[PDB]
């Protein structure tokens, strides 16, 4: 598919919008850890 | 009651929850009872109420309770009424790298592990961007192997996203930021746990790679394709008459 597949990659390269790629469907965002203490600066 | 619980259980983002909801209810009741506490948009009337509720019952934790102009005003009023790698020696915090890791939507355990790595080994540094970038990239490659396998397009998209987020046009430096951290972080038990969990082992399964490297010819190099692939592909030409 050497001649066509490269065209497929080239055409499909420009299509997808970088903004809307949802890497995980059902994820809950990372909050702020409460305490500063546990992050000891050894 | 719905919005009260919505905001109260927003603190994470036994007796604590119950006592806090009771405290918020009665505090809002006291604040609205008299005609002395008006011109207060409910848009934000469940934040320092929660702060002082934490202050009251048994224990209080300063961080991430105020997490602004009118915040202090309301507090006083109520309490009286009652490229990115050339830069050298940069600084970082918990939430900065938490944000950088959370732009992928990765879990919180991985972010906490990266933060622990940073706060333990951030003393002899030259540029923390490199280490954090490498850490998050090698977390993405290990956890997202399934979708990368089923779609070889992801590789380019992820690399472009992490090349634009750090404002660079050259990428071999990013490649180094990956391989060097892989070299450095190669022998830790939590890394071992992550490896056994998400089964990358260089992007290939354990039970296949052992036979791939042991010196056999039964090793399953999948130039051919799986039977279910053909079974589901048949449908595409089943309806070719249209």
Image: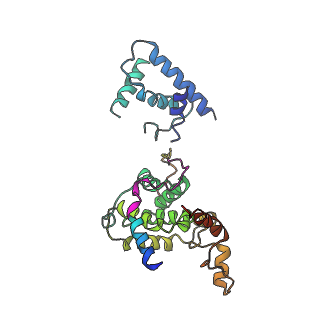
> In this rendering, would B197 be left or right of B123?
right
**Closer-to-camera residue (B105/B87):** B105
Colour treatment of the image: rainbow
Of residues B193 and B137, the one drawn nearer to the viewer in this rendering: B137
Q: Residue sitting at 47 percent across and 32 percent down? A: B51
Which residue is at the far top? Answer: B35
Q: Position of residue B156 (x, y in %)?
A: 43, 67
Q: x and y percent of residue B192 in the render?
A: 61, 67
Indicate the position of residue B170 as horizontal and vertical percent values: 33, 71
For image coordinates 50% across by 31% down, the residue present is B55
Q: Quadrant of the C terminus of chain B?
A: bottom right
Dominant secondary structure (helix, strand or loop) of the stretch shown in magenta: loop
Q: Is residue B7 above or below residue B110?
A: above
Let me know if residue A8 is in the magenta part.
no
Residue B115 in the image: state x and y as whole percent.
48, 57
**Left or right: B40, with B108 as reference point:** left
Residue, far front: B241
Q: State the quadrant of the N terminus of chain B.
A: top right
Task: Give residue B79's quadrant in the image.
Answer: top left
**Residue B2, placed above or below residue A35:** above
Q: Is residue B205 above or below residue A15?
A: below
Q: Quadrant of residue B238?
A: bottom right
Residue nearest the viewer, comparing B188 with A12: A12
Q: Residue at x 45, y 31 (%)?
A: B47
Give yes or no for residue A28 being in the magenta stretch: yes
Magenta residues? A14-30
């Amino acid at each position: 598919l050497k001649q066509i597949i490269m065209n497929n990659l080239k055409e499909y390269k420009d299509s997808t919008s970088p903004g809307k790629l949802t890497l995980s469907r059902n994820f809950t965002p990372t909050p702020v850890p409460k305490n500063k203490k546990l992050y000891q600066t050894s | 009651q719905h919005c009260v619980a919505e905001v109260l259980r927003l603190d994470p983002q036994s007796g604590y929850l119950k006592k806090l909801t009771n405290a918020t209810s009665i505090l809002y009741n006291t604040s609205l009872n008299k005609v002395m506490l008006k011109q207060d948009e409910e848009v934000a009337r469940c934040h320092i109420c929660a702060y002082i509720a934490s202050q009251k019952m048994n224990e209080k934790h300063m961080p991430d309770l105020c997490y602004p102009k009118k915040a202090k005003h309301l507090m006083n009023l109520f309490r009286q009424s009652l490229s990115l790698l050339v830069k050298k020696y940069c600084k970082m915090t918990t939430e900065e790298i938490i944000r950088l890791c959370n732009d992928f939507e990765l879990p919180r355990e991985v972010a906490y592990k990266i933060v622990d790595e940073y706060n333990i080994n951030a003393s002899r540094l030259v540029c923390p961007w490199q280490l954090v970038c490498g850490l998050v990239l090698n977390c993405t490659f290990i956890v997202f192997n399934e979708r990368r396998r089923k779609d070889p397009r992801i590789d380019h998209f992820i690399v472009s996203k992490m090349c634009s987020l750090m404002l660079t046009s050259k990428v071999d430096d990013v490649i180094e930021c990956v391989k060097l951290v892989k070299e450095l972080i190669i022998g830790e038990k939590w890394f071992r746990d992550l490896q056994i969990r998400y089964d990358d082992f260089d992007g290939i399964r354990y039970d296949e790679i052992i036979f791939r490297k042991l010196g056999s010819m039964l090793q399953t190099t999948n130039i051919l394709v799986t039977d279910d692939q053909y079974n589901i592909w048949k449908k595409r030409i089943e309806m070719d008459l249209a």
